[PDB]
Amino acid sequence: MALINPQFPYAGPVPIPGPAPTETMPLLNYRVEGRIAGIQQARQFMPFLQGPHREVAEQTYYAIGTGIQMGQTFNQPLINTQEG
Amino acid sequence: NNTAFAAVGANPLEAIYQGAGAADCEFEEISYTVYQSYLDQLPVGQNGY
């Protein structure tokens, strides 16, 4: 967006020496076929386990029984003959 | 007689007596008695105690 100087104008570009025209043109680089080499193993001996863990520990229980329940020799009360 | 007498310098943690004459100290009798404290005559209701 330059302003044209009317007192000192200039013309378009003139030819100048050039950079040997084939040396600015590249070759198209020619890929050969390739292979991810080797026979891959199916599994890996991992350093960490792959499953979930638990944040807190919960107390577990198992039921037990008591035993054969016996009789008893109670201390027996007195007879309510109007004193009680 | 090994754990109840400690010589001067040894750890008197489980010992009872400690002193210079502790190498010859002997027990004679360690008579003991056990008393059981329990609750008798449990309230049997239906299906047992």
Image (cartoon, rainbow, N blue to C red):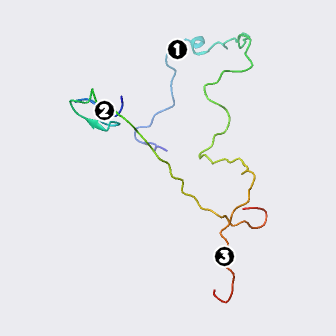
Q: Nearer the viewer, mark 2 or mark 1?
A: 2
Q: Is residue B8 above or below residue A44?
A: below
Q: Earlier in the sequence, mark 3 or mark 1?
A: 1
Mark 2 highlights which residue? B5
The number of numbered badges drawn on the structure is 3
- Which mark's residue is nearer the viewer, 3 or 1? 3
Q: Which residue is pictured at 31% across the width and 38% down the height?
A: B16
Q: Residues within 10 Å of mark 2 (few under 14, many from 20)?
A: many
Q: Mark 3 and mark 1: span between their CA atoms?
A: 129 Å
Secondary structure under tag 3 reads loop
Q: Residue at x 69, y 81 (%)?
A: A79
Q: Is residue B38 above or below residue A24?
A: below
Residues at discs 3 and 1 in contact (Cβ within 8 Å): no
Residue A13: x and y, percent?
51, 27
Residue that carries the numbered disc 3 in the rendered image: A77
Q: Residues within 10 Å of mark 1 (few under 14, many from 20)?
A: few
**Residue type highlighted by circle 2:** Phe
